[PDB]
Image (cartoon, rainbow, N blue to C red; front, side, top):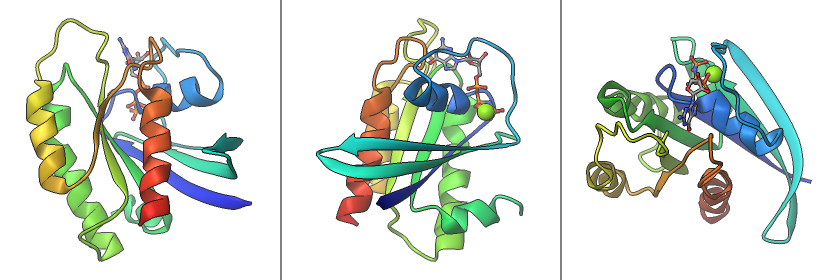
Length: 162
Ligand SMILES: Nc1nc2c(ncn2[C@@H]2O[C@H](COP(=O)(O)OP(=O)(O)NP(=O)(O)O)[C@@H](O)[C@H]2O)c(=O)[nH]1
Ligand SMILES: [Mg+2]
């Protein structure tokens, strides 16, 4: 079946793994468990198309080049209560542009942890960035499962259109 090679990238602690497990295992991981490299396979039906999501959950901590090269779509994740993570987005996208040799790659900017009240990054600020990159912006919470399916599915739709 049509495979989709998705890669979740972002700074440490922004909730990359949490967004992934909530999609596959349908539950929120409220524990300290830093990722080295984990891969998930799932048969799903998206817009009536039987496809398989081959998702690679990356570490937040030269070595990235390997999986960025084989990835088709990318979830660019930052935490809305962490300005540093939002700023680190630019570095990640730059390295993806470098290893892909492309200015336009299927990509979605995710603003995670939107359930928290201690926001430090305004949604307008992130939206302006997403506009500048030419990609969609979506706010999510792995805790309440808000926007989770929205984030991953939209990414698939961007690949289909690429
Ligand atoms: N309130 C809230 N907390 C969240 C959310 N998503 C993740 N967290 C939490 O924030 C922490 C970090 O989660 P984790 O998914 O491991 O982040 P990560 O970016 O994969 N870490 P790394 O890249 O280092 O392995 C956890 O303690 C976790 O439950 C969220 O959406 N809302
Ligand atoms: Mg992780």
